[PDB]
Amino acid sequence: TLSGERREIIRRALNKKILVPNILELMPAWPSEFQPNIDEVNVEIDEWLKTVNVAKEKKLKHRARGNYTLLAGIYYPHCRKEKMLALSQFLYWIFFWDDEIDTGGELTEDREGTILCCAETNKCINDCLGPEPNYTPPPGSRGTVEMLYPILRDLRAGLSPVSTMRLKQELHDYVNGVKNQQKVRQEDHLPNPWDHFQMRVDDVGVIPSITQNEYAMDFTLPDWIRRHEAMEEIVLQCTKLTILLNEILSLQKEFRVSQLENLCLLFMNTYDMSIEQSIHKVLGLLKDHYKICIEAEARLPWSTTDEKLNNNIREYIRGCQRLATGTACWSYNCERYFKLSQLNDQQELLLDLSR
């Protein structure tokens, strides 16, 4: 049964300590950097957060432990300072919004709660990014949608129409992924890891961060290149890298609230592995996707005559790669997932599944 399976996974992982190596060592050719104005942007973000209609205790906790201006500064280390505010605001939106509709959220176990939120959020995305935009939040707009209107307005002001179409669809995909994960018909067992992994790859909200590199660095990747098999592969590999490293780095946080649909725990449940063995297998898949991604670079349609085109290809894939390294680097520099005292002087993370 579901209850028996959960009971057993908690038993086998309870109070375990796992020493996790520095994940950035597994992507050594992909460097991490920090946008040089993060602190000054955070001063602006703190003033802006006063105007956001999200509960004060929630805003303070996200700001302190999440600190998403830092995440934007690692994803987009070479952007001009003027781009940082919108990029940082967007991350505050998506983490605030996800908080209400993720596995522990207010809306997650209510049919109308999820469905009506997704309807309102999809309408905002359409209102701001479609061909007849209206950026004014409707009078009844809830706080986590009202704040999205000016953010999308500002991002669209720095994006071409081609990049805007990608951002729009990627956001709908994220919102619809949330809506479609709510099943009227719940299964009496933990999911097969393959089914869970497929769901995460389709529904993770990170592809909008790749497209926002086109805002950050003020360029447009042409669709005919974006649809090339090697570029599709690079996007997919970096998406998978980000999901897998996030499964490891979020294991402690998720286990402590008994949220057991974590890929590491599903490996334990389905393949009869210890938690150490399961993390080791995830790290092995990380190494694989890093190598697959690098191999795809040689197949890209590089130009022999158009260096501006080549520069856009190079920046687009560096944005993809910084999604993977940046999510890891940020996780090692904030307290969303664990206390930073849990890192030692060799950047090894001592996870502690006590509760």
Image (spheres, rainbow, N blue to C red):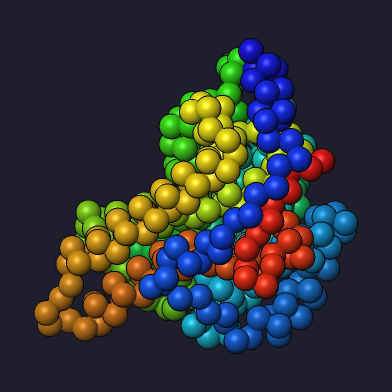
Expressed as whole percent of the image width and height from the top left, the position of residue 282 reads 48, 46
Expressed as whole percent of the image width and height from the top left, the position of residue 106 reads 77, 37
**Relative to 11, residue 301 above or below:** below
Q: Quadrant of the N terminus?
A: top right
Q: Quadrant of residue 235?
A: bottom left
Q: Residue at 43%, 66% (x, y): give it.
A: 27
Count all numbered tags in the image, as a single digit.
0
Expressed as whole percent of the image width and height from the top left, the position of residue 293 reads 32, 59
Q: Quadrant of residue 115?
A: top right
**Relative to 249, residue 261 above or below:** above
**Relative to 120, residue 110 above or below:** above
> In this image, 58 relative to 213: left or right?
right
Toward the right, the furthest residue is: 57
Expressed as whole percent of the image width and height from the top left, the position of residue 2 reads 65, 17
Name the one closer to the observer, 163 or 268: 268
Residue 323 shows in the view: no
Name the one closer to the observer, 112 or 127: 112
Q: Residue at 74%, 35% (x, y): give it.
A: 14
Q: Residue at 30%, 56% (x, y): give it.
A: 292
Q: Residue at 61%, 46% (x, y): give it.
A: 121
